[PDB]
Each structure stands twice: as C-alpha cells, then as structure tokens.
Image 1 (cartoon, rainbow, N blue to C red):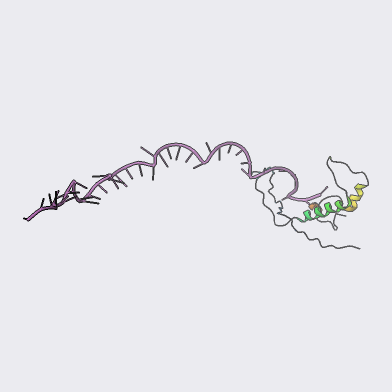
Image 2: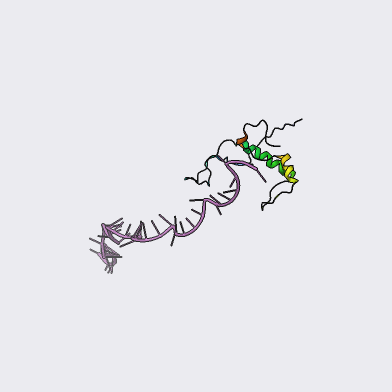
Length: 97
RNA sequence: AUUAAGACAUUCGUGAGUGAUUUAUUUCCAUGAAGUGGCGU
C-alpha cells in the first residue's frame, strides 16, 4: 500500500530555472541567462531524491568517495539507479525506488 | 543531485581649468563777519 503527500514550495528569495542557454556554454553569447517560469519535473525528482537521502544521511562529501556494498542497495531501494532518463520513456514503471 | 556549481558592476579618475566686485558718480548746493553808536541845546 502507498502513502501520498502534498508538497508545497514557497520561494524564500529570487529563483532561476535554466533554459537551453546557460552562462558558461560553449556557444557565442554566454553571458545572458533567462529563467524559465517553471522547473522541469526532473528537477522535482532530483529534489525529492536529494531530500530523501538527506533524511537518511547518504551523500557524497568531497573527494569522490566510493560507497560500500550496503549504501549501494540502500540507495537502490531509496532512489534507484538513474535520474529522469528520457530514453526509457516507454517503461511501464517509475525507474525510481 | 535537479539544462547544475563557481563570480562584490568592479579598477583607474581632484568639480577642476580660465575670471580684480569692477564700471559711472565733484561732499556739493543756499548763505554779507555783519549791526548799532551813546553821553552835557
């Protein structure tokens, strides 16, 4: 059985959502960045995954530390393998734990 | 872990240079140093 939550986001300051043109791309005019009005749903997914491991205290802190083969499947059962990969759009399941 | 992260609109810069408070203007106009004699027909 599943548990459902309503998550409300209140901005504490000015925000910005990146578009196709970002301040440090290799293209020509890489000094003007414009903000999309909404975040991508992948950003929402990354938000939830980050907070989920924050509550469970499982992060990468500094060097590129590797994780022992218990944090590995705890992150499997927590968030899964990948980010929102649009390649697997025809998959009849969320690829996230 | 999310088209992310990182970045003082900052460095240099005298409100400064040129410029008489000067020009024009009579301390002047009016005006008597003057008036009277007095005493014994």
